[PDB]
Amino acid sequence: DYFPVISVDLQSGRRVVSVEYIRGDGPPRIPYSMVGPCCVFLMHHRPSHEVRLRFSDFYNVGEFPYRVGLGDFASNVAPPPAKPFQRLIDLIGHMTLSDFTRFPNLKEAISWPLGEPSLAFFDLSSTRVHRNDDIRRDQIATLAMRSCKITNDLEDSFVGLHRMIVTEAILRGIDLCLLPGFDLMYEVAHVQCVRLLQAAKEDISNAVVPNSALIALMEESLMLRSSLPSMMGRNNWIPVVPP
Amino acid sequence: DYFPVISVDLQSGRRVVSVEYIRGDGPPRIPYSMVGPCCVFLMHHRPSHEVRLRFSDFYNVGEFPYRVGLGDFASNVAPPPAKPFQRLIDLIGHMTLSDFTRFPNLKEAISWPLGEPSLAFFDLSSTRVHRNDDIRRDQIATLAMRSCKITNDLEDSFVGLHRMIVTEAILRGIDLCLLPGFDLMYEVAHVQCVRLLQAAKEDISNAVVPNSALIALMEESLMLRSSLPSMMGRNNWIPVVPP
Image (cartoon, rainbow over all chains, first blue to last red; front, side, top):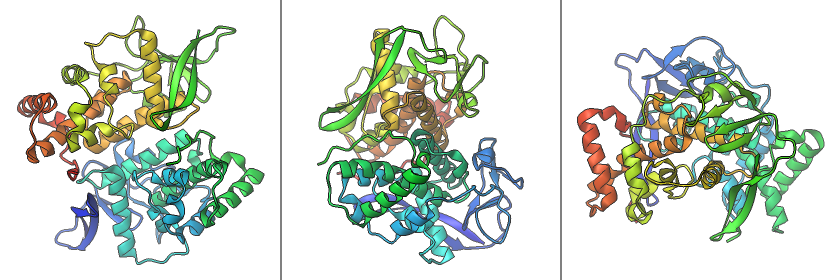
């Protein structure tokens, strides 16, 4: 049906990876998987039709779930109990990058996982943004590839992105019941939200002038402190020296 | 016996984490582990005395090996089949950082995992450098903490460092039989060596003047191409635009 084509091109004085899905049938590939809208062709992983709790429960044993995510089907990775930052994500996705890079700690918080500030995962996780499925799949695969900084393999990019998510969750004390690999863009945006909530403390401690970003983050922090403080992660954020 | 004390201090205009081991007995802590020379006190992980093949076989089930590494004891993580880059590591550890940062691709290759160029893991993995065990343990714990960029937990720093190693191994096609968590500094230096070998191709393709670094890397690449090409990883290195 659709083949991913990975192309390394020069943009903004940086050589960056992109993925574009192109129509082509011939004989369709037999081993394949659907990670959200993205079609992945499995070279090193055996597709599996079992339903398991975590994405890692597949790729840790050399397998790959048949199909994952929301849709007119049954995901082979059982959905998380909740997506508790979805309101904050919807609120951030309608904001510009300059709202965060003006503050150092917020910039550092959203630097992960691409190594540069980026609100792309917030846009792809928001429910109040509407995009075609083709552009969505291209952007999701591109972000998975750009997180891992490789050029050739796409299934390993999704495995690496989930592994990065779980590593940051373990470091920041995020509960792993909420990050099973169901909707990888939401997991990245969730961990970025936890990092943002930890960074906003240092930003207000540095006596900055709140914009909409800090107002939203402080409202969320207040509500969470009242209801479920442990959801905000651990307090192990390195303050960023102001330039 | 020795307690790790984690201190976040300003150095070189950057706020950075350090770990220093300080003598103190009182009642010694009951749950504890030895990762190499480093003493780790387990809050979230149950110590285990079983012998397993991978470090991940412990921390993936909420455990932590009793003691790991070389020494007058039996490591609870079975040693790797080989440490095949030890000669290259010994050769690189006697070199200065400026030998790599002069080339862009080598600088990018050794940027991982700390996000900045660093030969610290090469120094701590080399066999032809001699250091006291106290300074060694301080440096190992400091590097584990600085890889993860957190400030408070030390066992989670070692778990995160191993998870980062395995993520990069999976991305670069490195065989995971060689990275079980036995000597984490060697694993970091091994993955950095694979990245360096992949980057030296682009560096010579950019027609640079070889220094000792490129000479050593090309000799190793030639020997490996003759004997075991698959040890050099996959050819998925993004070329770095020359500044």
